[PDB]
Amino acid sequence: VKIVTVKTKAYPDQKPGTSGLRKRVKVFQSSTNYAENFIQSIISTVEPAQRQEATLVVGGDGRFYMKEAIQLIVRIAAANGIGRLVIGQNGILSTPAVSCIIRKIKAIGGIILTASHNPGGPNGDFGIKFNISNGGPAPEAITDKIFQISKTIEEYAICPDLKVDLGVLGKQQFDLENKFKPFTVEIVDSVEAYATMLRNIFDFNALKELLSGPNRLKIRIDAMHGVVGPYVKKILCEELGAPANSAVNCVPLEDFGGHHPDPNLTYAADLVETMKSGEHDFGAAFDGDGDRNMILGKHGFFVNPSDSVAVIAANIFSIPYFQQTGVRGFARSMPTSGALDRVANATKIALYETPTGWKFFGNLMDASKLSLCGEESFGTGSDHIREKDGLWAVLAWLSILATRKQSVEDILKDHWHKFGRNFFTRYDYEEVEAEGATKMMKDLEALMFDRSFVGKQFSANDKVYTVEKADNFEYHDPVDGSVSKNQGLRLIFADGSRIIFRLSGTGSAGATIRLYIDSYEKDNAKINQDPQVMLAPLISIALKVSQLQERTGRTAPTVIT
Ligand code: NI
């Protein structure tokens, strides 16, 4: 194979986010050398002396353009001096599986080709996420270095002629012009190392009894045509014995069947209606790359993401891994509800409240301070890998149903009557006019930081809300030293209720308002009544204090979660 050097002209917009670089498919296939430039920049962060012995893992969610970009990664990694590439069969590898293999075989890191729940196909998105040797996403120091290189790059090395068959398992060796060591590409089964790790975390025998036995839990798992479909089939159906019909949408499609792979009540509607029937005991959906999940009980019973980490926390010792390893700590992002706190308080186990994004969870896990973490945005994880894991959360729930022998509906009722209930809801006000929003935030801040703000009585209907604390949440990471200021406007009431305003805006189009409402309840009787009814006083107070309808006009929210 020959090594060619291509003279390239650098790009200004290739700044990698926390989830790597994402741009619509079109930018990648039209902008000459966009992909090649970025890939050579990722490889360039690996210094020469380390390339021969380095192994990089490559894989993706299977959306359109994935195969063309993997063939580009191979040719540039090969010309650049990287000794070996472990590619998942057909290029398919979920984000939890790539994290698992990097750690397993001690790789330098890996390149994950996914834009998570963002749509796929000719007119959709495409992303290139870079993960490091601990198995987790590359930290700011590394993402900005890639960004410094991309803006000033003049040339990239490539083996144009080299091509590998992604469908054939085993080792492929290639010789590169004048170079003494051959380039090795290893095609690995997409599910095997991942299922082997899960085989030692959970008790696949209790689960084989649960899914196959006389009692047989009837489940419906929707993989929304994304990467976890091969995994559902081989692990839940072939190994655990769930009938073939338990796996819906489990064949990776390039456009995700047109529709977005986003695990929620709106996008996973087809599964929510199939669940409403009553035939199934448990239902579940996952996103494009498998690190997020949605849990459903009989008759469509929505198990809120914030309640879900709390239930797994309140029964964590039902899982063999936690029994043999112990629980180092619990954690959640600040917008997420207080249910995990009520479980954490019942034990001498530490609870961390972190801002939004994996980096916070990853750092504490690497510091051996975190075992189970959750987010209100359909995210659940543990320290078994350094990424969230959607299928791990489903087998953790099936292990709890196996142990308990109760329904999902009953596990949450018994949970709310022990720990009390955190009625949680999230209001999304997608893209608004920035000035009004910043006023709504600034005036609110001023009003929150007052002498008479604290301790005061706010009230409407059922409850009396007294302002115990009020701020703009900031975090000082204990591991990397970072400080993340003004992460969110908090309103904390003395009973346990809370209102959180988060402004996720854009210096490109406008600004998104996110309103999260967490209201605590302890009464045995009010605990089971509907969340929109019970949360109404605080939603009206949130609009009356923020004056959102006043400075932005909008009455109703775009999305309700
Ligand atoms: Ni994802």
Image: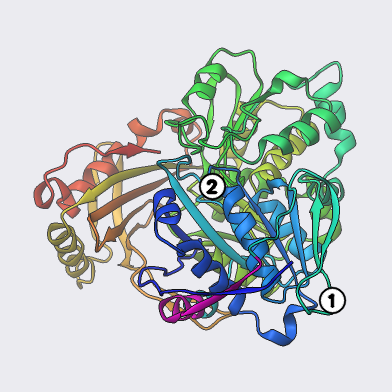
Q: Is 193 in front, or is 450?
A: 193
* Residue positioned most to the right: 205
Instruction: Write down the region rendered in magenta.
Output: 145-159
Q: How is the image coloured?
A: rainbow
- Work out whether 28 lies above or below 369: above
Q: Position of residue 538 (x, y in %)?
A: 29, 44
Viewport quadrant of the N terminus: bottom right
The amino acid type of the residue labelled 1 equals Lys
Query: What residue appears at the point 32 percent right and 51 percent down from the top-left corner?
Result: 514
Which residue is tagged 1?
181
User: To which residue does mark 2 refer?
Assistant: 65
Count of labels in the image = 2
Q: From what the image shows, is residue 441 above or below residue 182?
A: above
Secondary element at tag 2: loop
Q: Is residue 308 placed above or below 218 in the rendered structure?
A: below
Earlier sequence position, callout 2 versus callout 1: 2
Residue neighbourhood size for the residue with mark 1, other residues' Cα within 10 Å, grouped as few (<14), some (14–19), many (≥20): few
Magenta span has 158? Answer: yes
Given residues 349 and 557, the one toward you in this image is 557
Front-lying residue, 145 or 331: 145
Q: Residue at 68% of width from left, 46% of height from top?
A: 92
Q: Residue 347 appears in which quarter of the rendering?
A: bottom right
Q: For residue 385, what is the image quadrant?
A: bottom right
- Residue 27 circle label: none
Q: Position of residue 389 (x, y in %)?
A: 65, 49
* Left or right: 203 as drawn, with respect to 525: right
**Answer yes or no: do the residues labelled 2 and 1 have beta carbons within 8 Å?**
no
